[PDB]
Amino acid sequence: KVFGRCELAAAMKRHGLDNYRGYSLGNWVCAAKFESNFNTQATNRNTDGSTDYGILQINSRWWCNDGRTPGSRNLCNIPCSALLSSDITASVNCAKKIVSDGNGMNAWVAWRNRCKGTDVQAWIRGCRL
Ligand SMILES: [Br-]
Ligand SMILES: [Br-]
Ligand SMILES: [Br-]
Ligand SMILES: [Br-]
Ligand SMILES: [Br-]
Ligand SMILES: [Br-]
Ligand SMILES: [Br-]
Ligand SMILES: [Br-]
Ligand SMILES: [Cl-]
Ligand code: NA
Ligand SMILES: [Pt+2]
Ligand SMILES: [Pt+2]
Image (cartoon, rainbow, N blue to C red; front, top):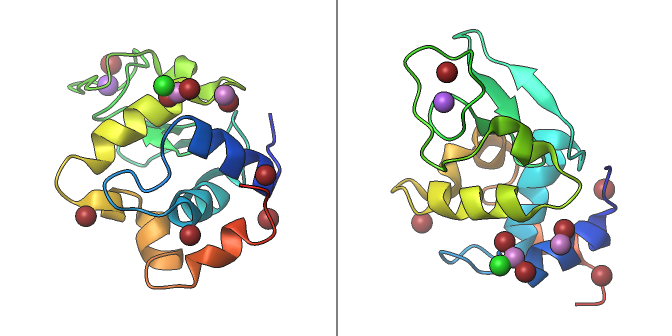
């Protein structure tokens, strides 16, 4: 599924991501925009052999099991395929664990490089929240 901007903002708020660990909804929407362009099915292989999965491009090295990332952990205790659902619940549950890990949203390199420090409020501008 390819979410619309306000549609994703609504889903993210419903699942309690809005201001989770202090990160306003626009941060989460911005991270999703640049991680996956809002596409729940996005996958991208990393040169280390891990793969990133879903709307928030959660990595198999640490967070989910894809059965092909040797020596990896599955800290969210989920198949990475679960992170490709049109329903964002598994992605949100895992993101909450990731962002609580100690480095906040810096764990998302696209958020650090493209969202951090920016007017992230723009991402929810106009949305009925
Ligand atoms: Br957009
Ligand atoms: Br919910
Ligand atoms: Br915001
Ligand atoms: Br594996
Ligand atoms: Br959803
Ligand atoms: Br959730
Ligand atoms: Br933080
Ligand atoms: Br909305
Ligand atoms: Cl929930
Ligand atoms: Na893994
Ligand atoms: Pt939902
Ligand atoms: Pt939820």
